[PDB]
């Protein structure tokens, strides 16, 4: 590890409090893409010009064309990348990637198979995995490791601010630090269970008064690429019975008028209770007894070995500015502002 004196920031767009993405450039001259920065995965991919237009997702997204880039390096190894909400497939390529200040030579997936559900619902084009090399498909070096190798970042850390939803900043990633403008009070740290996954021990989940969930302890994936807080089908059907909420296809709803008096939900991480108020986890889009309001908490059964686990996504990170510390293998939380 070599440390320099560089901090680099990426500005994010917030779409409807569900999608947070920024821009990268790939190739010479730069081809620009909207990407989610996802601590829950370790690969880079964008849609490829070689994607058949029978994938409607490839008609509606920006496609990388290797034939327009003088800095492209062929590889051609096939790979498949499995996300919580769906799967993409394609092949490895190498090119120059620009993110914030920084230019890095990077191996990434050119995606040629991009299912319409869910990718026709994506405002973003692809993904930049901020996870560890241990979970990288094809054992490809992740972008942050490649950036650390350059020895220009002040610290072996990166940080996420996600805003609530023209003039407002949707969010901000800091590579090599934190922005004290977007948090207050002190960082509280939890150690990773292990290097290789941004996953920490959780000691309990309260609904108001009572620890009625994860009573014997459980896992929390701190997942910048997940919209919601997620638990297993079994944990969530309990949480949602206790909130008086009903299942739609994939999510849970409450009568809009009941939203504001739903109880506080607390997550016990390291020393502290991380408390969400109903305003933090209800899409309070109306106060009518005659409309339904979605909850920013749903069921996700993440397969072993990472899961079963909770995932703390944008619902959580909106309240708690999050620092991901590779040097000391830990996660810091502070109150966002
Ligand atoms: C693809 O990339 C990997 C990782 O560096 C390399 O070891 C492999 O030989 C490459 N294959 C081709 C065919 O260029």
Image: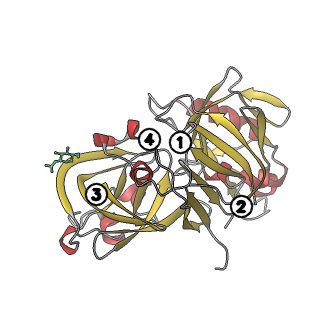
Q: What residue is disc 1 on? A: 326
N-term-proximal mark, 1 vs 3: 3
- Bin the neighbour count of mark 1 within 10 Å (Cα to Cα): few under 14, some 14-19, many 20 and up: many
What residue is rendered at 68% in x and 32% in y?
A: 238
Per the image, label 1 sits on a secondary structure element best described as loop
Is 199 situated above or below 223? above
N-term-proximal mark, 2 vs 4: 4
Q: What residue is disc 4 on? A: 132
N-term-proximal mark, 1 vs 2: 2
296 and 39: which one is in front?
A: 39
Is 322 situated above or below 304? below
Q: Which of the 4 image quadrants contains residue 162?
A: bottom right
- Mark nearer the viewer, 1 or 2: 1
Per the image, label 4 sits on a secondary structure element best described as loop
Q: What residue is disc 3 on? A: 111
What residue is rendered at 56% in x and 61% in y?
A: 7
Q: How many marks?
A: 4
Indicate the quadrant containing the C terminus: top left, top right, bottom left or bottom right: bottom right
Gap in Å between the C-alphas at discs 1 and 3? 29 Å
């Amino acid at each position: 590890l070599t440390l320099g004196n560089t901090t680099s920031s990426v500005i994010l767009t917030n779409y409807m409090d569900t999608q947070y993405y920024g821009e990268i450039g790939i190739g010479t001259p730069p081809q620009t893409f909207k990407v989610v920065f996802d601590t829950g995965s370790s690969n880079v991919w964008v849609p490829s010009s070689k994607c058949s237009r029978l994938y409607t997702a490839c008609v509606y997204h920006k496609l990388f064309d290797a034939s327009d880039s003088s800095s492209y390096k062929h590889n051609g190894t096939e790979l498949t990348l499995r996300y919580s909400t769906g799967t993409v497939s394609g092949f490895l390529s190498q090119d120059i990637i620009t993110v914030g200040g920084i230019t890095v030579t990077q191996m990434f997936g050119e995606v040629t198979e991009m299912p319409a559900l869910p990718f026709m619902l994506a405002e973003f084009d692809g993904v930049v995995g901020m996870g560890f090399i241990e979970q990288a498909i094809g054992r490809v070096t992740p972008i942050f490791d490649n950036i650390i190798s350059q020895g220009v970042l002040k610290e072996d850390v990166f940080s996420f601010y996600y805003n609530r939803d023209s003039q407002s900043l949707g969010g901000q990633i800091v590579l090599g630090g934190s922005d004290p403008q977007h948090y207050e009070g002190n960082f509280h740290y939890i150690n990773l269970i292990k290097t290789g996954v941004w996953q920490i021990q959780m000691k309990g989940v309260s609904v108001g008064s009572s620890t009625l969930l994860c009573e014997d302890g459980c896992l929390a994936l701190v997942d910048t690429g997940a919209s919601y807080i997620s638990g297993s089908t079994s944990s969530i059907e309990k949480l949602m019975e206790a909130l008086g909420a009903k299942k739609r296809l994939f999510d849970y709803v409450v009568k809009c008028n009941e939203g504001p008096t739903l109880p506080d939900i607390s997550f016990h991480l390291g020393g502290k209770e991380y408390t969400l108020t109903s305003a933090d986890y209800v899409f309070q889009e109306s106060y009518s007894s005659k409309k339904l309001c979605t909850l920013a908490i749903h069921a996700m059964d993440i397969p072993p070995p990472t899961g079963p686990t909770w995932a703390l996504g944008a619902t959580f990170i909106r309240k708690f500015y999050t620092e991901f510390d590779r040097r000391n293998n830990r996660i810091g939380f502070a109150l966002a502002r």
